[PDB]
Length: 138
Ligand SMILES: CC(=O)N[C@@H]1[C@@H](O)[C@H](O[C@@H]2O[C@H](CO)[C@H](O)[C@H](O)[C@H]2O)[C@@H](CO)O[C@H]1O
Ligand SMILES: [Br-]
Ligand SMILES: [Br-]
Ligand SMILES: [Cl-]
Image (cartoon, rainbow, N blue to C red; front, top):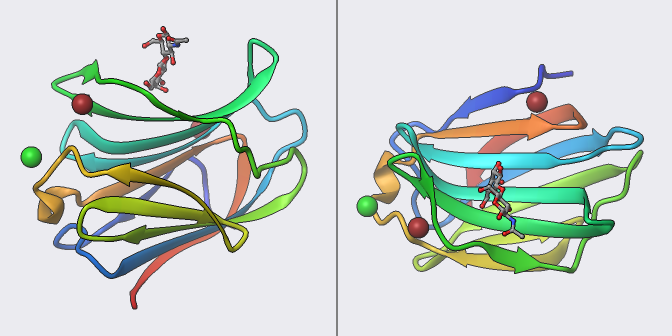
């Protein structure tokens, strides 16, 4: 098992065709999960499943620039379940991050931070047991 929060360095940043795969299991009674693709202190792409936001499950995506969060992009389709194993795959495409969970497409997030080669770390945190975090080029 890997320790959470986990930092996965992305050498030389990301680039189209790079696929990041995370495998883990949601804790029972989980409250949140977060993936933070970072460019230094900025968060190019924050992916944040929330298990109980005003008694609703929602995935919130955003970007943090100079310590300020921008406009949130929300997705009500919620494929995660407390206590169950999951697979998140994030594929970098030219204009967006494309996310699939358990092999089903979930959402896309348009690139706000354009210096892809400077998004050099991925932080994985939240209420999960982390099994694997890796990348490959497809
Ligand atoms: C309904 C609403 O406006 N909610 C927002 C919260 O989402 C927001 O929380 C922060 O959200 C960012 C992502 O945008 C990130 O997940 C932070 O961890 C989280 O604290 C909150 C504070 O910015 O404002 C509320 O208005
Ligand atoms: Br922004
Ligand atoms: Br954590
Ligand atoms: Cl930029």
